[PDB]
Image 1 (cartoon, helix red, strand yellow):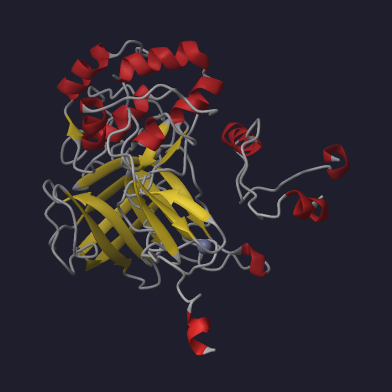
Image 2 (tube, helix red, strand yellow):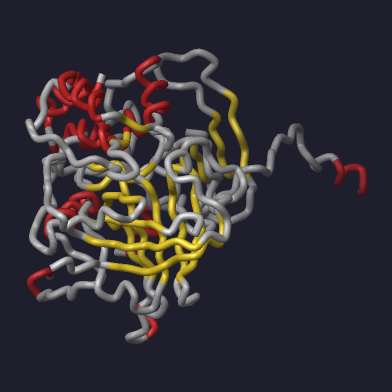
Length: 150
Length: 60
Length: 49
Length: 144
Ligand SMILES: [Zn+2]
């Protein structure tokens, strides 16, 4: 029942990816309110006009119709199930493409890092154990954000 | 003895560009080529060769 | 083999054209078998030998 | 010279570069339009790359549709972008300047010819090996 993969409220560190940026897409840099975990993500600024230092709510779910399987692709527009993390302002579908860590130090694996891709859109999440339950997988995760310009 | 010693010094040429790094020796001791004015379907490329440790690669 | 190989290539270039790119083949097995660095690597080394 | 002889060129090569751009976005209507152009297709519509504020597909998603679904080519973006040898390593925002495809799905990377063919490390050579000439010819005709 709605076994959410991740949920947190994030703060914008930067909206200017190394200055040069791009036109329809821009890379945001964020950090979690725990201030122990940080995030960088490519976004469509045209459909979601971000401001710097903004307070965002971020949620991640590998599934919708609750917890049951759906990793298919009949973009069934006609679904009517309220099992939709839809009330959030911004949603994306993607894969995890890379995982970082460091287990050579002995058990370590200290400061685990996850990298994620939503249709090519790169993402980086850093954290000791926040990603201890996740790993790199084919496209399945849904990323939902709200609280824009709170 | 100096002047006859000087007669080897440079030899007769020079080049070097020192722009591209070489992953075999970190030093940018590289040479560059301007070739393929027209050629066939292959795109005109700039070829870079590292003198030391012999490395050659392309702009592409 | 490593000791022999120094004789064969005085140029020290290890990049040669050869048949069957095992790396791509081995990699494909990983893409197929779904092996990952956060999964155990159960192996019998003699079988490899 | 143990290399491929085929090569997609000019207009086709330029639009492919254009197509790999990050700013590429598609509409559902055009996706159906694009799907019919396909010389072959599973008959099963793919999931939108974006759902909110509005449903969308990416050109990289769609290029990856063209790609056969169990083969990958890596390491050679071969474009000027990013930097020569250590800048792109400069953290690993692996970025759009380097090419990478997984399970027939393009992760990032603006395309080049060294990728596209008549060279070592090309997608064309490995498809020929795995998919064979017959599958590769139909893919090639289809992409063009
Ligand atoms: Zn060198």
